Amino acid sequence: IRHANKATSSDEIVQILEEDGVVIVESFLSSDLVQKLNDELDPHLAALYDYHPVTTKQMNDLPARSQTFRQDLLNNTLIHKVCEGFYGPTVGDYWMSHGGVLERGPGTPIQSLHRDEAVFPAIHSLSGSGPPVMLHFFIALSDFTAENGATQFIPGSHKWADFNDNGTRDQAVTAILKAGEMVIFTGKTVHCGGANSTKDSVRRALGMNFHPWYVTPYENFYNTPREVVESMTPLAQRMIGWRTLHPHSHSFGWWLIRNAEAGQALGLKP
Amino acid sequence: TSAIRHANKATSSDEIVQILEEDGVVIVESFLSSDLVQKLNDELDPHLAALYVTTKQMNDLPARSQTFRQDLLNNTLIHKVCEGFYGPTVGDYWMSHGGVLERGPGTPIQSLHRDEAVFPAIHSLSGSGPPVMLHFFIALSDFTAENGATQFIPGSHKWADFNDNGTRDQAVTAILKAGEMVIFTGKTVHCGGANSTKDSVRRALGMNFHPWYVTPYENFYNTPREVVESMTPLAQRMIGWRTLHPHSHSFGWWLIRNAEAGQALGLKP
Amino acid sequence: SNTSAIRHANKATSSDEIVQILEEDGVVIVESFLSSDLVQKLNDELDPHLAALYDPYHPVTTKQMNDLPARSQTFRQDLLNNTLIHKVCEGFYGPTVGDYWMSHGGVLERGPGTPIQSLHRDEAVFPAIHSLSGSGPPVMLHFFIALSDFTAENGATQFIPGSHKWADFNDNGTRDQAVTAILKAGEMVIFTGKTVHCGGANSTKDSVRRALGMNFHPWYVTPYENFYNTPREVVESMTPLAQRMIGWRTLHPHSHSFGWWLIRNAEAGQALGLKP
Amino acid sequence: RHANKATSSDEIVQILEEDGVVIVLSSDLVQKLNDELDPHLAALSGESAYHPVTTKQMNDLPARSQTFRQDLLNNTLIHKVCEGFYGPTVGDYWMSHGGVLESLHRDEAVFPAIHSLSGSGPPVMLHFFIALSDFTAENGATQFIPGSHKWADFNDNGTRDQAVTAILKAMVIFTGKTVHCGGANSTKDSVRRALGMNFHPWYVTPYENFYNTPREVVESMTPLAQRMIGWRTLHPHSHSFGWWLIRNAEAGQALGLKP
Ligand SMILES: [Fe+3]
Ligand SMILES: [Fe+3]
Ligand SMILES: [Fe+3]
Ligand SMILES: [Fe+3]
């Protein structure tokens, strides 16, 4: 995997992503931003069910839960330029399907090599000729060691003609990052989580999985309190399904209410 | 010539799914009782008059029509044909668009087309693409070639190149009386007809369904809470208020905090 | 005998007796004017239009809507052609007037918390007519249909019978002289533009009072509403009587029998493409 | 081949003879045409239904457009090319088609007895295709095959290579014997708008019937434009006395028009 950032352009980042299926952007979040995210997130990780430590933890509905995710992450300029470059001419519009914080503690087993877009057999059966669907931004909230199980990737596996082949493990490259760095990959790229050999270290990450406008998001954000939705930018509101999408094909719009803009239809400002 | 292959009054739902597989279009006779057609027209007329050219379009039916809320969204034949059309790998489905269409005197003939062309990534797969759009076209009025009944090209959902829309001479007219329905795929070539009649307006009710993973055209979250609470859980899932359960991701999709969405926002278990 | 009220008119009452009660009292109640089905579709046709007007700093205790002929088919056909309304119009304007048309057709909604209205005469808007008080000519004829129940608790309209005959219209009376008009169904109250009246306060925390008013004019008084924007397809669906009511046909006063509201001294509706 | 004002009306009739297609309106007039025509096209609720209308056509222009009624039907270039195209033996002509429009074929295929004669057949259709919007190969320029009007066999429609794209900014004239086809509109935002005027010789039945035009619209037009829409009798050189008469008298005068 290419650990390329700092002087790298977003067009370049899109190019490494399309050639390899995975890219590492160094120092994406400021260390203060990482500390702000962990501070806002810790109480809700502790409250997940209101001598048996819980090794594995998964949490979503981040916009309701974190202000910095509400504002900083959903409006991040690099994530949006990479989304526009990844979806390209034919797609047009996109939104976030899943935003989740992931925690593996000590003793977590090794994961199977897999492709996330396997959840869509109708898309997954086209293998590498298939349209771009899933785009995954995997952000740091703890150190990524091979020892604590940093996620592994097989570069170029997004282009294979047969997706029944998940490859073999010696083809996987571990993604080592330290601070609020990110790794981007497509839903067609083979990957797997690592085993956490240390007895003393918990792996924490934030994944943001985006979809094209025409693929159903995994998360429903309509129970998000109205006051917090009104505090968000219209771009972030479209990302969480509160605004209509604008595909280039049928530019009149999609996800409408009475053939009119959706967010205005249920009380948001125009 | 090909003809449309009419059905119903003794055909099983499996037969309708099979006719849909082979021809891409089928006519279900006597689908709605005359009383149901009269409720539907009575409930829809005031909303059509306030919509502000004889052509008309209207959606957001569940807020506007009780018969659509209860009778149509819970219709057993529609759901049997839906489960037969999407089949094993899909599992769950929901409604993308429910609309009343009105085409009165002077209406121009439509160009031959395929509705699934609004999805270029799917449309470019031509006949080998997955099932996506399933359209139920109910006749709230008589469908005559004189008033512009929809024409179809059977077997065109099968074609290897969807850049070919076929020719107007391969088209078969769909004559429907009232409460009769025509079911078709989003991959089948079709077009609405010209309404020469100086006097008569054609009324149809379209119900366009999607597999679980394709975004519905309509958003129903501004639907009033007590009309949603009056609906059956199946009908609530059709309008996006309940989580889907694809065979692919059996644990669920369209969730709130990895929990059932309708329960999460105050609906009954 | 010890007590007096607005007089009711039942189905066995003729329109001549209704016109009689109307210019002895200035107000009359026509029981069971609209069938429950007519009230139901009238409310049904009006609901989407009101919802589009009022869906969006201010609580809404009050709603109004006009331009009914474009908006409601039952109003276009059933109400605008209603035989009793035309009998009473002919009797109210009488020989010297001859022809009449509708000045204002409006739906009014008074919900909870609406304050009591001041006593008034609707014809104060015409000072040259209003200054003649009870000697003045008939001008406004108001038909107020109850689209919901009219209770004193939700503010049923109050009237002062005989106030249309008063010699000084600067005097609007006092609330102790007003009698409430209780109506249930699509029952109607007819009153003159010279009779003092006022809407009540809606004390209820739950109930909305809804009414449909049709205010008619003699041919020579300018209607409040202009109906030029009514679509031609809906005007062509109307009967010639209803077309004259909304100003698309010439009037035929008894005074100037040749006609009024003409185009090149010819019938107006034919002159702009309607059927002869 | 393109033709400016240094081009003769003669020399354009001589392209039409040689190639079968020619490329030659005030931008203001173009906007006036678009302004008068837009409300009628919109009226074809505002029917979209997530299903926008892609192909559109409209006719009966004289009832609908004043500038088409006066300037276009009386335009000196259309009539000079019409007289030059029909020539001596024909004499008189009228409009068969006035339409706004937004496979290889030949319009004179609708006349099998004429179409069977191939390139030696008499002139019938003359088609003026004006650009109400930009005419690019990117939004689907009508393609033409020059010289196809003279081919000895009209069941050969040629192949899609011989097609030369007709690029216009804001008309192209062609015969009903020229192979042509409209292009595909790839542009994912723009729509090409054209106005076609298809003329016939006097003896060929026009496609459009113009009697439902209200009488005042007919009476405001020049006598030439009234003859173009079938309200005046034709005067063939063959039958110099007249054709399309009422009781052997001029038709438009017989039904209340001018002398
Ligand atoms: Fe994964
Ligand atoms: Fe269609
Ligand atoms: Fe008043
Ligand atoms: Fe052509």
Image (cartoon, coloured by chain):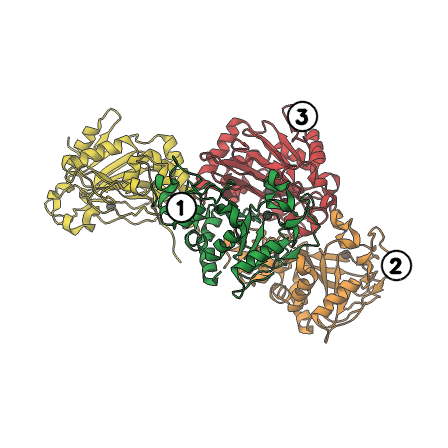
Chain colours: A orange, B red, C yellow, D green
Q: Are marks 1 and 2 on the same chain?
A: no
Name the residue: 77% across, 58% down. Answer: A55
Per the rendering, the mark at residue B11 is: 3
Residue identified by numbered label 2:
A169
Identify the element where label 2 is drawn: helix
Name the chain under label 2.
Answer: A
Question: Contact (CB < 8 A) between labels 1 and 3?
Answer: no
Q: Observer-nearest residue: A107 or A90?
A: A90
Between the residue at mark 1 and the residue at mark 2, the CA separation in whole angstroms equals: 66 Å
The residue mark sitting in front, 1 or 3, is 3
Q: Observer-nearest residue: A245 or C1?
A: A245
Per the rendering, the mark at residue C50 is: 1
Between the residue at mark 3 and the residue at mark 2, the CA separation in whole angstroms equals: 54 Å
The residue mark sitting in front, 3 or 2, is 3
Between the residue at mark 1 and the residue at mark 3, the CA separation in whole angstroms equals: 46 Å
- Quadrant housing residue D163: bottom right
